[PDB]
Image (cartoon, rainbow over all chains, first blue to last red; front, side, top):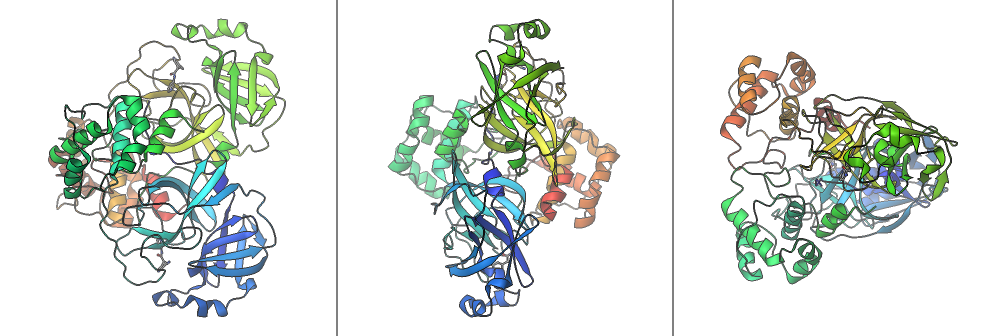
Length: 304
Length: 304
Ligand SMILES: N#Cc1cncc(CC(=O)Nc2cccnc2)c1
Ligand SMILES: N#Cc1cncc(CC(=O)Nc2cccnc2)c1
């Protein structure tokens, strides 16, 4: 019993964190096999960040200008290349702690764990979600760039995010491990505004199922609805539209609790229209949307 | 920017998790040096749990009855002893991944990270606090016993909790690493009720300071108060009394923000009396109390 915002154990990723310094800029790198991945803005001075031409800035850099340190020991850089917004620094030593891994590009609404680092050293781990506007609400200070987001399936780490930027509003933007930003963001110190941060409806429903499994049932009502009726209310409350694919994904939770997905939608619809009335669900006074249906099943079944 | 419920990186603790089986009961153990620590209720059948006499049950157990497995390899048990509610199994091999460590007994209000495990395998990490009634609100299923709570100061892990029990209300109870329960709980399948779960006032104030540092300032008001006036309102709302020791501990946050501690108390007093009015602070609709002043400083300064 109990339901917590839970991150994956971070050990496998801690073994990959390195410090990358170029000139006077220091950030984090991810060392997998004999390649260190890091945000390409490591080559920029704060002045260059205003309007950088990365290809031009990279011409003035050689392998020896990239300083990579793993723990208190230096790695030898024998090659470097830019792939989209990340630099790949080939080193002469394969990371002995390289876990089994994949690079994945996640969809909005998907959750992942972040190992926040400074100077190639891990400081903390937290769970978050790719927002529908392709930002993430993280906890990152100057020096955190290159910190990564990941999910783990038994022994294989799927890396899905690398931190690059803080928008003027204090929300975060980054890339997948191929260097492509999530959303329309660019690695430039220019004002970029995020779109509407809508609520991830399928995740709220999964979390309402987690609440029922854990004894929080006060919000269950005597109504049902349809996908079209629910979605009219969802649009009004800036919730993402629910599709039959989302209903399918909630099937295991529906089966476990005996609550039809559309009945849970009707409970959610009344919570949107009536509010919580000072009550809480799983210790929260608002509807939580950073647990996917897969996360609820995993946490409630104890997947290791 | 951004403020997250952040756990310590769990790698150092992942390297200590083992599976302990006695008869038909399997739970988690913590392997430090040549000792494996685990809840003494590993020797109980579900029937024994109703009214166990641990000393009597232990007479029927020998070293070879305790099966300890680290990864997919078996450890040889060469000694066993009971210390309060934990068993200490001496093994013939010192854990090669033993980090620098201490055993600490925390006070209510203190926070720590939990590495939730099943069959000696880590499944997740989350942050929580020792409640003022000496329970913890965790996320633990059958098989999670022996999962541990810890804090890390640079490279030294201070273990403060080991999971033992779920109360009939779904809240959790456990011991320090010397086997002494936090609070009045006992390792017996008998109905035990928790006392009032009051709000950790000094932590709410620390989190209001974190909110100001991150731009959430709407709740700042034009008032101040005194410790005695604030505490009259705190008692009424089931908040822990604030002492001058708490005011002292909030000094660094007061200095950083320029908001006197008593002025922040007056903002908190108005939030208690007026409510949030549908507003949020750091993405929360209720006042968060599982961040200590030390956690706020650490997260806001990027301690690794
Ligand atoms: N890419 C990119 C980029 C562009 N302009 C500026 C930066 C620096 C930056 O965003 N800093 C920081 C600070 C706190 C949290 N996260 C990131 C990065
Ligand atoms: N000590 C002790 C004890 C006493 N009676 C019963 C138990 C078993 C128990 O509490 N199970 C469990 C299940 C889910 C989360 N946490 C713990 C343990």
